[PDB]
Amino acid sequence: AKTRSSRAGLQFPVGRVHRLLRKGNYSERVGAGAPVYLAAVLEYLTAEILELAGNAARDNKKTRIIPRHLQLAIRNDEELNKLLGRVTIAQGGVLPNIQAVLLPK
Amino acid sequence: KAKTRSSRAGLQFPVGRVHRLLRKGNYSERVGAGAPVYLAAVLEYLTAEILELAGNAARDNKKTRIIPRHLQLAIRNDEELNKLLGRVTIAQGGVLPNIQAVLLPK
Amino acid sequence: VLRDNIQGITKPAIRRLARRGGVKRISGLIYEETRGVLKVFLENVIRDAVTYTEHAKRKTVTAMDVVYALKRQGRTLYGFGG
Amino acid sequence: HRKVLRDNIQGITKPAIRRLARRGGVKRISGLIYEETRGVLKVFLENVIRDAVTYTEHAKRKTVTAMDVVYALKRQGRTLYGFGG
Amino acid sequence: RKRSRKESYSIYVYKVLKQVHPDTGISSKAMGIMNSFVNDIFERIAGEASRLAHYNKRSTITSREIQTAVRLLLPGELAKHAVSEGTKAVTKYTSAK
Amino acid sequence: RSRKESYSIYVYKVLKQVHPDTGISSKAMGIMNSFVNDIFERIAGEASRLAHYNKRSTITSREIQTAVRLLLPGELAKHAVSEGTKAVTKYTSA
Amino acid sequence: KPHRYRPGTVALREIRRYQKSTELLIRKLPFQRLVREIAQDFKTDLRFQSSAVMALQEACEAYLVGLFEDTNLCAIHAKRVTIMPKDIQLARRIRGERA
Amino acid sequence: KPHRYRPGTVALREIRRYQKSTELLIRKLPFQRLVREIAQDFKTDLRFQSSAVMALQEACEAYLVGLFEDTNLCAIHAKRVTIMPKDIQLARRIRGERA
DNA sequence: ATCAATATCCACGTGCCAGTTATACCAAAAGTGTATTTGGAAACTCCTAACTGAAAAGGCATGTTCACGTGAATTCACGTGAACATGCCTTTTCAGTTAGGAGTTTCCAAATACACTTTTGGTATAACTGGCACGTGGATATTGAT
DNA sequence: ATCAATATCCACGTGCCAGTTATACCAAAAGTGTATTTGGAAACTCCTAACTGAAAAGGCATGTTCACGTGAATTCACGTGAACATGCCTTTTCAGTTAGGAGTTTCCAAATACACTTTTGGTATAACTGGCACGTGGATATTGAT
Ligand SMILES: [Mn+2]
Ligand SMILES: [Mn+2]
Ligand SMILES: [Mn+2]
Ligand SMILES: [Mn+2]
């Protein structure tokens, strides 16, 4: 009696991802390798964002990740910024950027 | 006597085929009988709206046969059809004649 | 005092938005142009959200209706469910 | 058995780039434009072909089909009519 | 072996053309464009209907879903006439059975 | 008599796996909840069209992989395909 | 006697202040009344979740801020520092929203 | 004695000429080589339907003509009539391709 | 204004191929009719959270002074357009070779389908606390006038 | 350059709420175990169309010369946003009453699911012709030199 998530070495629920594949009308049949594979990719991507966001939280000397930290983690990583270029982060803010020609001296 | 559902609904587009592709496409588990009829009527109307504006463009060019250029002139000159097909490209379509005014001489 | 609702977006508020966008100098005619753009945007989104609300046979526009509406415009939004 | 292929972006000649700019309603063209245009065209072509070939691999095929190109363009947001559905 | 039947909308585009312009023909290229248009508009509407029924936990795509999809996807005046043509074909289909 | 699913449990577990001394606010937790659902939708959708284009009735792990290549930029694609194939091999042998 | 910063310094001060922060810049109540007026012209007697109004404020402010970024680029492209209505209209025509 | 049109007359003549037509402006054989080269250096031993190359050439020229239109707007916005690489870069930045 | 030089619009006349037509083949859908399953409209009732109201706080509007950025004007160097001579590389049309796409058949590993058992995730009340917003003084940095 | 006005961090301490924690149900999934169905991987062969090549022709590409008009550089005047102080009104922050979201449950019109019949759409070969591409000269419009 073991869940498929531990049998695959993941923290994300493989059984649920299998259920959402069936009830989402994506196709009539779902092999068991698909929810495991998809659950692995969702956990990996989640970890990559949480890592960079945590570093942003420490660099502002905070211990808890707020949306601002997630925004700084995404808009500063090139590939994450490409994946979510058409996404708006609530309570995210903008990256500090002043065009050089506006500066004095 | 058998009569097709397309004549039963007074349409020129195939209602039965539109029903099959709705099931075959995994858009939902069940499909009522109104959805294939309704959608078939919409596709036929939009087809008619484009062929009306295209044939006029073909006639203005002294041609008796529609070519993709006429379809391009039809879509790009009708605001609502142009908004519906903004991110679309017509093969062998061309562009509308447009010269920015500041480039003209004198 | 009577004034339109589009004027509730006050000139210091539009100025604050431009400052977050890195703008240094703002012409006067911008403030009316910005209000017009802000209205066109809100009109397109709410019309789609309301269309979702009617189809659910509801009378309360929900946060998911607006999220699905923004998602339809290509303006995806994270952090309000779904 | 085939000749090696290299530096084919130079086949996109300066007159051909000028014609595309004329149809775009451009009257005067700086000299530095033609290389910048080649750079843009190459990035575009790479992105659509990369996706087109990926569909071809998944189908276990050795022939890139026009449908693979259409799917490629569609998922880039460049929907194209006239080469199959 | 006989090659498979490659379906298209060539017949029905040609019918609708003869209704609208009875003395105008169409080239195979333009007919190819029209085939791409019908299939494109089909997948936008049917897809938007699929998401619509899913947001409301419904397992059926009814003509009510197709209509709300049309309201969301078509621009103003084109949506008005399209909803009209759709409703007429639906009620006429109902009364004839 | 109501139940709202989310991914907050597993996002928090993964958070503790990478930053054992870091918490996460509720707003930031809702953002991660949207990100998991969006990325699921894009992958599952692209996989669905892949199965359809080739007249297939099953979404297999091979489809999810091809969808990952098309959706994820370069290096993110390489590591995502790896972690995916790693978890599938481990699931099959066990 | 009165100390006055030269024109442009307070602005650059506001830029660093408002790019560092995250809060909403439009006031809630003017925005919420603007939403209900717009919603009324589509469907009468509508009620809104508090979260639904907030989701619209986050979405529209994010849209206008990103539009000022592209607007500012057009102004700098014309050897100016002042954003003008023709800058916004160029940025919206090239995005594809208008024309 | 010899007749010379002034600089710009034959340009505007061509603009009208090439906006009236629809045939492809890039050469067929150079374009097919370019496509095969790019495809080769991603995956080896690939064959192409003739239509597949035509589809790519259709989308490519369509993409560049559109990009030139937005480029032409950027130069006119800066009080010029000559398009320059910084125009193209501004067009692709606001579009979101270059960001 | 006059003028010639050049390109362009337009009707005419020409063969050829693409488009239209008609025949039959026909398997592949689509329609018909039966019995079967089930979703979701309809009552009903429960209960979040959306609206209404009244009272307190700091951000908005107005008006004044001026610094500087914008547009208009003028110059000049040179880079880009226009023309032509030169000839190469693409276009065109045909032919035959075979890779590989695509059809058909067989058949098994892997999917779904039920009933059944096990536990995990979500909710809720109650509890808990330390991380962060916020206030402060006081030291440094910046900015602008002399 | 020396200063003075103003903004800006920085280190420390403060209460408070949202975050973390834990406990208890428990229905809802998820897992298990069985019987059942089936898609699609594998053989094979058919045959479309992609690749290859030869050879001739002229439509364009290349590169040079040369002049002109555009872009960049520089000046300059004035008018419009920025800065700032002030006066105050709208926004912000809290309470208790029901609209409507959302749950539960019944049951009927409507959906799927089978088998069977019927015909519509697609392929094909033969057939057909007029629409359209191409080539031509000629009348007209435009352009640039004068
Ligand atoms: Mn190579
Ligand atoms: Mn072979
Ligand atoms: Mn000049
Ligand atoms: Mn038939």
Image: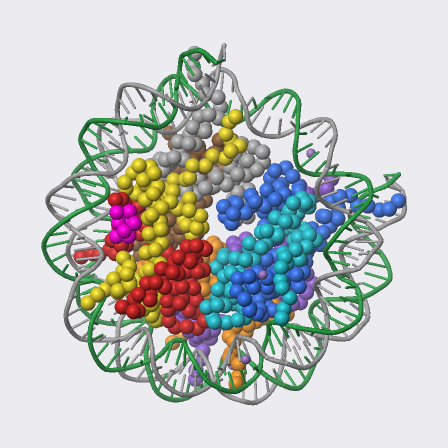
Chain colours: A yellow, B purple, C brown, D cyan, E orange, F red, H blue, J green
Q: Look at the image and tell me in which quarter the C terminus of chain E lies.
A: bottom left
Q: Is F15 included in the stretch rendered in magenta?
A: yes
- At 58% across and 69% down in the image, what residue appears? H48
- Tell me: residue E93, above or below residue C19: below
Q: Is residue J62 left or right of residue C71?
A: right
Q: Residue placed at 42% from the left, 57% from the top?
A: F77
Total numbered labels: 0
Q: Is residue A102 left or right of residue J146?
A: left
Q: Is residue F79 left or right of residue D76?
A: left
Q: Is residue F6 above or below residue A89?
A: below
Instruction: Tell which quarter ligand 1 is in.
Output: bottom right
In front of the other: H59 or B34 = H59
Q: Can I make out residue E60 in this image?
A: no
Name the quadrant containing residue C7. Answer: top left
Residue H3: x %, y % from top left: 84, 46
| J10 vs H78: above or below | above
Q: Visible in this render: residue E25?
A: yes
Asked whether, in this view, residue A55 is left or right of residue D13, the answer is left
Task: Pinpoint residue J144: horizontal percent, then vertical percent.
Answer: 82, 43
Query: Foreground residue, F43 or F21?
Result: F21
How would you classify the magenta stretch by its main secondary structure? helix
Specify whether residue H9 is painted magenta.
no
Residue at image location 45% in from the left, 60% down from the top: F70
- Return the residue nearer the eye: A83 or J25: A83
Write down the region rendered in magenta: F13-20
Residue under the point 21% across and 65% down: A2
Give residue F23's position: percent from left, percent from top: 26, 44
Is D46 in front, or is B92? D46
How far across and down, in percent of the image, does residue H31 sit? 63, 61
